[PDB]
Image 1 (cartoon, chains in turn yellow, orange, red, purple):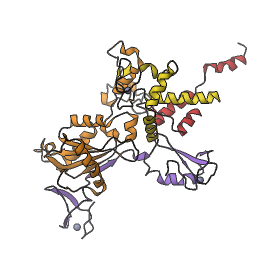
Image 2: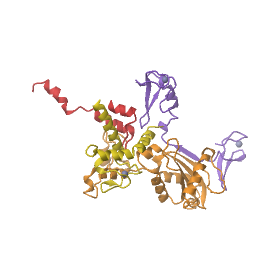
Image 3: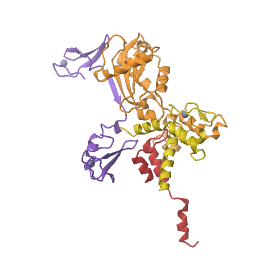
Image 4: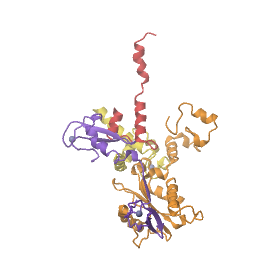
Length: 78
Length: 193
Length: 48
Length: 105
Ligand SMILES: [Zn+2]
Ligand SMILES: [Zn+2]
Ligand SMILES: [Zn+2]
């Protein structure tokens, strides 16, 4: 049960951060300056790591979760 | 064996030994080294540069296009296609939201209506203003109108490009081209932008 | 199967430059490769 | 097209002073009002649009060669559904013989 719950959370975070790797939630691709995108709050050291600083991974994810959900639904339609 | 990476059989050897031109190459590649030895260390910078250079023509963002014999005047009611007469609702919004982009005085009687593919606009991460600015910069002999950037499915994003009379004045001494032929040729240029 | 479950729920999102069909095929080809530890039972059944 | 009211022929479209004139080979000429202002059109991704698979999706629950899935139908409460995967984006649609269709269709 713990394995399934942790795997669900890890997979969901991995999909979210693989989607917003180059794609920017604010439109276009990321504009990385000083390790941080100017348009959004993405940090370079968070795209591939979701364990070292879990507080920051839960902050960026919470900001653009909805936008993410609508985009995910829209892709899966028509 | 897929198109664009065909290395099956003896195909790359034939391209070399026959001295075939670049147009006849089915597996051409290229390796680009980042100008900054510092940037080349980090993969996110390398990944965003790699996605920065990827030919997205205006054609692949389109679901369907219609070439309409219409002119736009803001005040006078001009005739419109019955299927797209509902487009007038977002015409008015565009004019009050773009007081600097008023329609010119030399709009020809030729209109191109576009219906953007929203899935490709999401998968490729292309904003509407990126398309509009790219089209306006490359095509000055046209007038471009569009709807709002909508986040709700079922409501499309419509790109409507009106041709100015200066498009036909470019080369009309070559009389073996009717106005319909220039207008269609304008469609091909705009799509391949 | 876990890739199929993601597909059925619409959890598979391809990167830029790949369609969902191509990304799903890339995942399925990678997930169906034998590990290096496949020789542990092979080598335990034989005397070199 | 425009069809001549006299000989039911396909008229030729010309443009004069900002108006469309359909002229036939029998001399009859008419001018289109609104429905003839469509010079040309094209639609992309024709091989994966919903209009292509309408008959197939309607017939999917009855084809015995289609993949089934162990998932309840929310309408008739049958315990299996027919799953189909259409398009290059691999769109999954669940259908039932009662008329239920995931994606609300
Ligand atoms: Zn960003
Ligand atoms: Zn006639
Ligand atoms: Zn049912």
